[PDB]
Length: 48
Length: 48
Image (cartoon, rainbow over the protein chains, first blue to last red):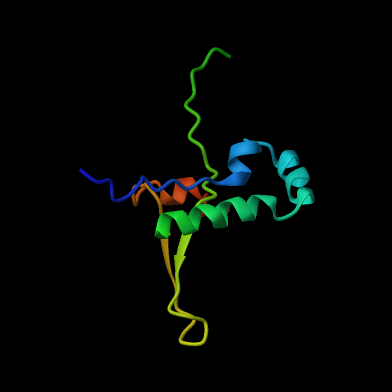
C-alpha cells in the first residue's frame, strides 16, 4: 500500500481572517502580500 | 417587529478565471467553485 496524493485545500485569506468586515480588509491590505504568498504556496501543492 | 428573515451571504471572494493567454486572445471563461448556476447572481450580487 502506497499513498499517492493528498487532498487539495484552497483558502481565501481575506475571508478567513477578516470576516464580513470591510474595515478589517482596509487594514489587511496594509499588511502587504502576506496573504498572497500563502495562497500561492497552496496553489503549488494543489497542482502537484 | 417580530419577523424571522433568512440571511443569504452575498460575498464570494473565490473566483477562478480561465484564460488562453492575453497574447493569444482576450476571451475568458469564469469558474465558481462549489456553487449552483442559479445562486451565482445572488452570490456575487451581479445587480450591483
